[PDB]
Image (cartoon, rainbow, N blue to C red; front, side, top):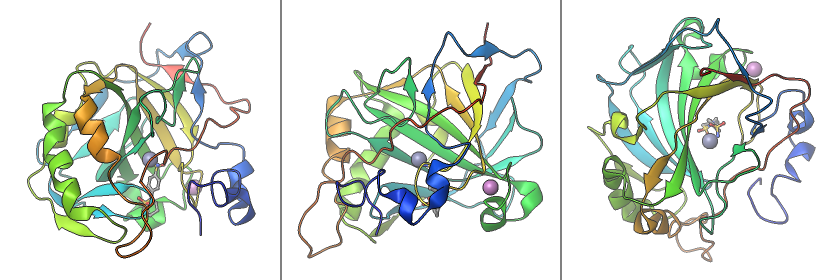
Length: 257
Ligand SMILES: NS(=O)(=O)c1ccc(N2CCCCS2(=O)=O)cc1
Ligand SMILES: [Hg+2]
Ligand SMILES: [Zn+2]
């Protein structure tokens, strides 16, 4: 099955998921000089004060911090979005080295990691139905660079010992996603896709201009995770990012002048 290795990685995905070569695939390079400021964009609203985290899961390609999405408790609205999108989970993509790891690039620059806060359009009733829709999802993407520690990340870092291998999960209640956000909500936005199989073209991407900083030791613990299940040969969970895909005649919009 699909992975990030030489034999099952991004170059292979198209054979099982033909949409890999579609018209609105993600991630993309954000060419900052080609991006246009959009005055019709409303202010971005991130409402995570009532957020209810439940669990953290190693799914064999990254780890998901899952939330209770049965009521409007953590929501994303405004910006390019019509209606309300509920937070279901967040996860990261990272590299084997600090000079790579992000999925989106900015003027071809790769960051050490990228955080994805995944949201589904409430008019569609659940996540499964939302991913059948062109505007089913909204993913808020945040770049990670190496520098000072992110205090709001440490609770995540510390539990990774407990979910080392594929299929392992751990209780992860009372985690506050607000501690993962940068100061500014300035962003780029474009229509795109899931960056992993099934690569469904359902996402409004909202990628924040301001990266967060994480410490070397925080990122190092990400790299100690395993792609494999327990009792199988160890394959370090690193370089779980898809490279930039063709923009194809889509326009990236900026929230800022
Ligand atoms: N990387 S991404 O586009 O934000 C992304 C968001 C959600 C998902 N998933 C959809 C398939 C089932 C659960 S999931 O987390 O793996 C995969 C990728
Ligand atoms: Hg879709
Ligand atoms: Zn992702």
